[PDB]
Image: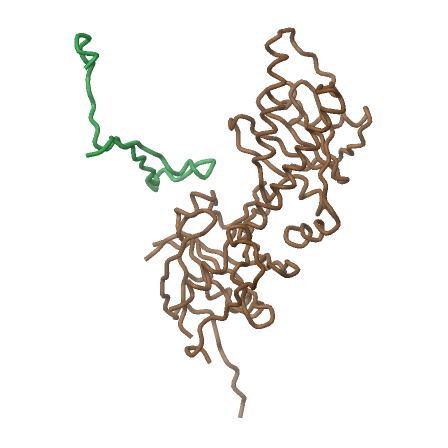
Amino acid sequence: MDAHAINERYVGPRCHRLAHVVLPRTFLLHHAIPLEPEIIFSTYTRFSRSPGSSRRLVVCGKRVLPSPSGLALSLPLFSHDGNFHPFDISVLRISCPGSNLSLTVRFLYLSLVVAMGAPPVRLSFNPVNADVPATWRDATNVYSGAPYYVCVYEREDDWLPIPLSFPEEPVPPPPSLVFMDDLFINTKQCDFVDTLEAACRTQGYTLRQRVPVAIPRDAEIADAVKSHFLEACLVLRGLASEASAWIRAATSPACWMDVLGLWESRPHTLGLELRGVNCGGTDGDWLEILKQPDVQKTVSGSLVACVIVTPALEAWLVLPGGFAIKGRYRASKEDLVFIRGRYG
Amino acid sequence: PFVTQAARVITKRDPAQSFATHEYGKDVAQTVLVNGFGAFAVADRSREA
């Protein structure tokens, strides 16, 4: 409970209002946040019906040992031109300095803004104190459905409620404006698969080898590799994720790779970087791909497809057996301003 | 009661044992079959019943 009062003196002035938030373990078990003291938190908000980006801020968080119990934080709220927007996502990014861990925790303002509603000369001495009492108010996250607590500390204040500026007509439906990100990436993924299915039609519904890997002679195995391509089309369409590989390729300033979990036998790991491999498409460059430990098991093994994305937004779908199909993510110039603003 | 339901109980481990590799390894689970019962082998002469 110290991290609320620390942030009001260092993150506090650099914002407009703070959202004091305490996360219970039921929220921590869902988003899988391993509570070590090494964790660096980073916060930024994604605006709507405006050019969407706010600056990134580092917020301190401490475990509260016991009346709730859990991780304690403070979220920034930004008021451009004197008011809040209701449909305006505040993104919490959790990462460790050394290891491989990146988690995105997303909050909406209407779950926070509503939850806030009820002789030598003298030098001043103002230390950080937990003397101010807390008023615990309940909330639910819209995205996960796990409850989290909100503090309200005591200090033209009691006269007015918290200003909101609701959107104006014509407006898309707020089930579609809340999930602005998951309906943008899903249509890019569904247009990525349509390039792969068009590439089979120009070749005559075939799958050509690219990687020299010997195949044991059985007719059921030749039917099994075909089943890896159709299952990967059920996955790439159904996948709509914030941290996909092509998004890192669009906001890169190097090949970007993410393996897949076919038939739900694995969870997806997204955004793996190929450091030191230049995907030029020549037969010299595929050997540098094969030195990776992932690509050897996506091809010799089974149940895992693999997607390798160039910085020119051209991507191959690597199947087990060495088969590959060139595809292309189509991102317009208006779309790249939308992606590099909110994400990168 | 209605149809017998399965409620799974996930608790934190005792603070002697709170050391694990992954984050779910601090929690160990148990299934409690609510409104059912345990039973031996039913006779084969009335298996249809």
**Picture residue at 19% right of the left edge, 34% below the top:** B1
Picture quadrant of residue A259: top right
Using the image, determine if residue A2 lies above or below residue A125. above
Residue A147 x/y as whole percent? 39, 51
- Residue A164 makes an appearance in the image: yes
Q: Position of A310 compared to A9: left or right?
A: right
Task: Choose between A126 and A286: the one closer to the eye.
Answer: A286
Q: Position of B27 compared to A52: left or right?
A: left
Picture quadrant of residue A291: top right
Q: Which quarter of the image is occupied by the N terminus of chain A?
A: bottom left
Q: Colour of chain A?
A: brown
**Picture residue at 64% right of the left edge, 61% below the top:** A50
Colour-to-chain, green: B
Task: Choose between A330 and A96: the one closer to the eye.
Answer: A330
**Picture residue at 72% right of the left edge, 26% below the top:** A325
Using the image, determine if residue A39 lies above or below residue A311. below
Q: Position of A2 compared to A227: left or right?
A: left
